[PDB]
Amino acid sequence: GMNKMVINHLEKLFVTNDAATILRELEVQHPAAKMIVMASHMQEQEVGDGTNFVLVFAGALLELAEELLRIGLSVSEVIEGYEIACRKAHEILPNLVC
Amino acid sequence: MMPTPVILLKEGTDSSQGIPQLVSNISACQVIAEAVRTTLGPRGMDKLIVDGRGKATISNDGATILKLLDVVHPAAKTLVDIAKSQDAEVGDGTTSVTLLAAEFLKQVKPYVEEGLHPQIIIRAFRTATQLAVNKIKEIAVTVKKADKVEQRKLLEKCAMTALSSKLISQQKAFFAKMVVDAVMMLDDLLQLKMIGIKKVQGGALEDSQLVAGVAFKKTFSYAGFEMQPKKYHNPKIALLNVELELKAEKDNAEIRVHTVEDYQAIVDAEWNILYDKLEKIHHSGAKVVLSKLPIGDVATQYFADRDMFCAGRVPEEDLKRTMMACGGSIQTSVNALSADVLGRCQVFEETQIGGERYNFFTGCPKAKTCTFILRGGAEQFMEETERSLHDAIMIVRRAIKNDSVVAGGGAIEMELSKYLRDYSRTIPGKQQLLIGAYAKALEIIPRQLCDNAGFDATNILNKLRARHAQGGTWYGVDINNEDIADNFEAFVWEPAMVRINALTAASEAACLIVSVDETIKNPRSTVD
Amino acid sequence: ASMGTLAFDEYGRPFLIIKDQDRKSRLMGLEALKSHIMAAKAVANTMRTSLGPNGLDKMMVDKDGDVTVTNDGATILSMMDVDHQIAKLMVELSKSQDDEIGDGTTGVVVLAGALLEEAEQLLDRGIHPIRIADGYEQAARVAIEHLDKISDSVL
Amino acid sequence: EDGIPGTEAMNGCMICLAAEYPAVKFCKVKSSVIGASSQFTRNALPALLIYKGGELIGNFVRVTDQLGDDFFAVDLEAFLQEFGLLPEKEVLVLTSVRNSATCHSEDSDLEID
Amino acid sequence: PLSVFGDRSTGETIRSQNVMAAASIANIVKSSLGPVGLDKMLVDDIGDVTITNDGATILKLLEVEHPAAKVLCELADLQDKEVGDGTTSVVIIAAELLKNADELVKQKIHPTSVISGYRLACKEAVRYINENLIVNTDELGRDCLINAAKTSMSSKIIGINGDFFANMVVDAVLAIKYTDIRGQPRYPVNSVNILKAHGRSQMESMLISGYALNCVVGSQGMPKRIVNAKIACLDFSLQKTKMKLGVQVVITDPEKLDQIRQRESDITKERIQKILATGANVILTTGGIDDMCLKYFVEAGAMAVRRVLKRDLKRIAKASGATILSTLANLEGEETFEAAMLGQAEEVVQERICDDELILIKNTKARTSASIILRGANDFMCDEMERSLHDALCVVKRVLESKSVVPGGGAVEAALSIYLENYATSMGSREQLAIAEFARSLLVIPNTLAVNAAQDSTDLVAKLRAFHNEAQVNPERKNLKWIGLDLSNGKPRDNKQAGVFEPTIVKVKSLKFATEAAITILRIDDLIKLHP
Amino acid sequence: GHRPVLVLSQNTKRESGRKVQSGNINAAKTIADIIRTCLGPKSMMKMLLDPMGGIVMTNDGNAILREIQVQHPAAKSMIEISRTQDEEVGDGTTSVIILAGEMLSVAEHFLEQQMHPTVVISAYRKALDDMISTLKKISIPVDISDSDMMLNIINSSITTKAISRWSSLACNIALDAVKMVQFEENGRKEIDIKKYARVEKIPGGIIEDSCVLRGVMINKDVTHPRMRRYIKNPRIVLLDSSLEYKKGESQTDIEITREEDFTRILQMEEEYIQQLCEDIIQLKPDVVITEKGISDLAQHYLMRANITAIRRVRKTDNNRIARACGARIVSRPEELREDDVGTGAGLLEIKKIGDEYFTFITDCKDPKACTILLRGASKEILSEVERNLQDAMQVCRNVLLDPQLVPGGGASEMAVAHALTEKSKAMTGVEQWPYRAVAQALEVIPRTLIQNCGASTIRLLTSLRAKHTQENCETWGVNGETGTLVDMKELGIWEPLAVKLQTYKTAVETAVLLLRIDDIVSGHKKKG
Ligand SMILES: Nc1ncnc2c1ncn2[C@@H]1O[C@H](COP(=O)(O)OP(=O)(O)O)[C@@H](O)[C@H]1O
Ligand SMILES: Nc1ncnc2c1ncn2[C@@H]1O[C@H](COP(=O)(O)OP(=O)(O)O)[C@@H](O)[C@H]1O
Ligand SMILES: Nc1ncnc2c1ncn2[C@@H]1O[C@H](COP(=O)(O)OP(=O)(O)O)[C@@H](O)[C@H]1O
Ligand SMILES: [Mg+2]
Ligand SMILES: [Mg+2]
Ligand SMILES: [Mg+2]
Ligand SMILES: [Mg+2]
Ligand SMILES: [Mg+2]
């Protein structure tokens, strides 16, 4: 990954590749992107790593949800399938410990 | 691009990404390097920068020039930062760091334009820097003799080399002897605040002197000060932090009396308190009294009647230097003025120095401090003299820490370039091009020396390369003879840590600049 | 020959390096030295009329309208409202001469102006200014030694 | 300027006329941009200005007085024609295929010899 | 001191400014080089949209202020005018040459030495190209022209349909072949009329065995199709006669006015009667025809077309054997029209093309003509089709005129770089550096080609240079001079066998023009910009 | 004033990279989404407000797109595609936009990954060739001599428009107009719906009274009341030249000296008019139609022969009358011939409709031009009816020129998609993914039909795909009114092969054209 020079509203320069720091310095205005940034910051607070994973996974999930909505599925069906698959993933994960 | 009714980031957010933004960063670093390029070498020049208020600063020091420029480019600020870092850690070479970093970026720019992955460039830079630092440590010349004469010669040569680029280069031997004398008197920490530097207008550069003791300017004498003698031949010095004047005993103190006798008693008690303090000071045997706090007119006249010298409102640093020079202790109370807390000096005198009176404490045999009194024709003249002396002092301190030297004038960098080229000739070939570019970028300093001196840099560089290839580690640029010479035998000596830190900082800055692929600028808040 | 540099990148993207770089001027190379020599020569030629017994005075007016008539070079240069930095350097040279000695505050400025005037024609012939300064230092040492040689002692 | 009645009708008329008169160079500009007087903006804002060779040939101001607020392209066309400022209509092909060539050199088939 | 009302930039500042301007112009079009390049879509201030890949069109549409950038744009225009291809390559090469020359100058190398080295390098590169890298097309046959057209049309909107468009281009060029004096065949391109009409797909574009007119019959009563056409080409209008400025009609006896007014149209009636009596079926005129003459032609059962373009009329007349007549005046002072002035064609048809009609003159005799009707999705795509088609026609004309071709894909650039790097060591001491920098700057073409494909440019260029160095050093490895770049797979490839060819004139002229432009810009070291 | 050094202009904007491609694709998607709901038998109409004050109420894609002004050049390209589709075949305007949007979406999917646009373009062209082959394979022929099948084709073309309520009347009108305007001369067949087959809309009355006239109707009245307004079997003469005395071309000033010359000149003007009228009368006609003015004296002299005269008729109307009544327009009356007289018009009658006079020539034997008289509720209703009739006539002409027929209702889309998917299984390259993606992008038509019908998109589309996986199910589509699968050889919805071929070609080439752009430059002066 590559570092990004981010200058905030106070002319302070940040050179980092940490996703949480980049999102914090960026002035995100869209409420949905604000919610995703909140999720990333919560992941940073709880664990301390994996914020970029959270962001990219949420983006991919929402893109594929848009595809499913376009092909004819409803929001409720997509949400139910996502929850079922998340439960399946959390069940599978302990078996993947090496 | 689409309007996107609700935008992601707020309006005014500017984003630049990809190869063009990194090429722009390299160009900005080139501009910053060019801003200080001409101030390198014995044939370097000075830059004059005027601030908003109208005051001008004239300097040859690269760090000062870079600080005075209001650089706002995020990538270009890294060069200023590494210049500051080199100034802090070493104190000399603040131009070479910027030149080397910009040359690294310029050399790797063509590979950036053709799509080479920045991680490969960063890895090559790290490998080349590690190899160069190891080579510098291996080939640096040190003497395992601990000879006082040899150490003195080494320090003086390093100081002259550090000084032979400034306006005081004509008196470089004299100033270097002064600097080495001053540094060698510091005890073990080599604190800079133990070397006072006073600038007095008027006089030639050769009129500047180093006081083996402490000297400071006269501090707002009261009435009756001119009635005091101004020379003592073995004075005991009372270093105090005491306000010697009639005043309220306490800020919250209140006096309540109901008799005129008690009123007179209170007035006499205030006078008696002041006179008791003065008598305790006088009975200690001291003839010179210095205080960090104001000394009133009553105390001044009292000391004049006793043929004693007084000076109030002395700056704290001057009192600390006086304590270190004489051997007393700053007393906040005069109740115990034993002989152990009184400073001693052989001669105290107040003399005239260019329309300004100065107090002199000389003859101190156990002094751990000095005081430079610089003479010049203008404020900026003396400021630049002080900057040059600071560079020399830092160099001498670092050499005191370790006496490892390498020949200057680009000789060390030509040797490093030859070594790195030889190493790069024996690797697969993707890293070979980048290490060769690093070695070529190492040639900027001798080329810049030749360009500043007005030579033909190409022929001198060719001769240097041929000499280094066939043997001879310390062949650099001979500025006076417009040729090449053995710079180690010409006593163009630098501490090895100077070039080590220069290479490390330049490589780190280049890697940081290369590693950035996107720049985002949030809109300004509270523009007012 | 001013304003610094302006490229705005070879990609069309903004190129801002120094704050207010479009409102800042810059002189480089021999042109700046020529301008400095011109300013110093102007100051020295102004002062050179007030030299010697037949020298004339300068009537100086401050910002409040007060009138000062004087022959002292240091006073004239201190009260003169200059903006050029080299002129301020000459003023400080006069002030330093006044501080150290107290007399000769006009000779120093004329001498400096003459030295820079000669350095101008030296530079026109392709000599590094550092070489000119070194030669000036050598000649100053020679002149100081000669002054010591030809001096006389008074009671 | 925005909001003053008659501006949108004039815009539609100019669109139609430019469709029918390619030669003319119909254009619009706000009074603020040209820096007109506040008096002119408040009282005489809707005005059609006609130029020809850098000099004025049409000085129409407050065209709504003699055109109204519901004037169509027919009204403006007739109103401009009756002062003889609008160039005469030239018949042209409505739409066709495109060629897009203009002379140049060596653009000449030549007999073999 | 100067007191000049303007701005002055001198030395390194102006040199860097010129280099920056040239580099910006190059970087504008560097993304549109090679088969993996992509088009650009330009929008005017009035909303007009142009989608193009041609460097000359991009630089002409762009509004440029810097003088060096203007020099580069005019260089692209000149390369388009004199060759027709390699418009992006010449600009890129010139900018790279200028950049490397400025890099040399910043090292205290005198600009005159750099200019001398550049001239020597250009001369030696031209000589080496002419002596080693040219391929004679005599042993390749018709496939060489097809391969050249395919190479030219790569990176264009018609690249994938090249299998069809190359045959169309070759047939169109061969249809207009003629030999002038000295027996040298000549191919007058721009005589192939190109008509653009949106509609059906690209593959249904038509090559007309004749001429195509963007015109229709004057009157609806005329026939829309004539089998055995006798074309009469006129350069005068057929309207009611009007006397000149110097002649005036003054009537004193009223009885003469009716006769005057009758003759006023009887003159044109008689002229048309003569023209129709000679046997003509199709009448084409550059002037207008009014209703009365149109009715004469309608009653005669003949096709009449008015306002025909002069170039179109000349092409039709010479293809059909007709003679342009600006007047029906002979050398006997009479008014006659002869059958020998009539052109002939196998058919003249007004066909419908996407809710519009145009006239096709099919199979003109005594000369073969060619026209191309391009079908596309919309107007912009048809315009890009026309530009690419013109590029292909110019390339085929250059190949047919001069029968030498060179391998494409950067093989020529790599070979020249290796050869000039070897050759620099035998000339001078600083012109040595100039020639070396010329050789290095010649590598910008394969580098840009590889970059546009997101391939490893460094490794591919290194492999190409190794192949060409082996070809130049080893004496029995001369077959490696054709090793170029295969951008589809990102590997070196023998481009002579693969069919990636270019006319030698493209490379030679691009080198010469780029060198001259670089020298001209490098000649500047001081700029005075007078205030307007 | 202040002079900033620039390469390009201040108002020149340049953007490039993934942003440009994404912006183009989203612009095309938005253009498609604008008219997504106007496709199918259950489409909903839209109100468009003209900048000139008019109102357009339609569900035709071309009108909706042409009424929208856009800034993004990709949207301009899409609108140009819509206009091209309308001008070429006259139908499928809404389908082509949706297809182009879907193809650009599935292309953006790949461009998000590291696939070059040229690979996608080559895959798209291969897919387009395969679609053309499959469409030609699954087509069926039609018998143009069968009036019932032609009426069914026109009906299936117009079932999606507002005129579908009066389906039989509209189909009969369109078929009769196209059939009678069909012409053959000199071995060149033509239809020419644009010039002849004029549609005249008179607001008021009922739409069931609309009919195609066996001749031409114009909005004209006799020049003078004494003219006959009803002629049984008229002989019609058409002219362009005015029937009035006019100035000559040359300057022809007279000079009158005698007394009687003025009256003589006026008398000869009258005599010239009389001579022209006598030359006209020599052919013994009943009606005289002129594109230009007719003098009052000319009217009198024509009345003396009992001839009805109409003046100031448009050139297109006069050509239509010539085609209808079999006359030839003559400029000079003295050159009139017998074969130029129009005999074949079986009735001429000037009747009053509303408060206006209309001239009817509507009993011609074998007329080659016609007037479609449309009567309806108002102006906008009649404009929509005229647009629908234009679509019907275009479809009829397409079938007449190309007698190939293709199943509708999305059946052809699914058949071609299945064939391409089956073909893609044997390529084993990197282009197979874009090939399959653009093959499956054709399913947006059945999906749009199901969405507009209001049924379940996913279940119906899955069932349709499963059905099309069978061995003979190429004609299985969706019923757009009930939202159920149905065989199109039973439902009867069929479309011309030309319309489908044009739609697919235009959509694929639009995607190819918009996939080739990565750089946008805007703001520069037109320079010309
Ligand atoms: N007498 C000399 N001869 C040749 N080179 C010298 C001499 N003195 C210093 N240099 C070179 O000048 C370079 C710059 O030194 P200087 O300008 O004093 O400080 P900085 O390194 O901050 O620019 C050093 O790298 C040194 O090698
Ligand atoms: N099929 C191909 N394979 C490899 N390289 C090609 C191919 N076709 C063209 N090229 C190369 O791409 C380069 C760029 O051509 P292009 O930019 O399209 O022409 P122009 O320079 O006239 O715009 C040419 O130098 C040519 O050698
Ligand atoms: N009764 C029907 N049932 C199902 N589909 C139909 C029916 N009638 C028409 N269609 C479909 O609707 C499409 C026509 O929609 P239309 O509004 O005409 O769009 P366009 O103008 O783009 O053709 C045709 O592709 C056809 O397959
Ligand atoms: Mg992590
Ligand atoms: Mg130094
Ligand atoms: Mg004096
Ligand atoms: Mg080309
Ligand atoms: Mg339809």
Image (cartoon, helix red, strand yellow):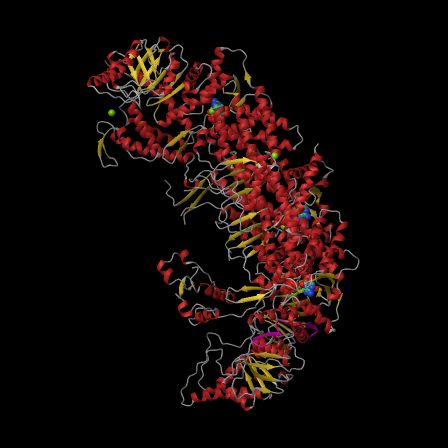
Between residues A63 and C59, which one lies in front from this camera angle? A63
Between residues F322 and C5, which one lies in front from this camera angle? F322
Q: Which residue is drawn at 40% across and 15% down?
A: B369
Looking at the image, the residue that sits furthest to the left is B260
Displayed quadrant of residue B290? top left
Which quadrant, please, contains the N terminus of chain D?
bottom left
Where is residue B132? Give x, y as percent. 58, 25
Report the number of numbered marks: 0
Where is residue B193? Give x, y as percent. 41, 20
Where is residue D8? Give x, y as percent. 46, 63
Q: Give the range drawn in magenta.
A: F182-205
Between residues F99 and C56, which one lies in front from this camera angle? F99
Looking at the image, the residue that sits furthest to the right is F471
Does the magenta segment cover residue B326? no
Between residues F459 and E29, which one lies in front from this camera angle? F459
Where is residue D93? Give x, y as percent. 57, 68
Which quadrant, please, contains the C terminus of chain D?
bottom right
Res F361 seen here: yes
- Quadrant for ligand 6? top left
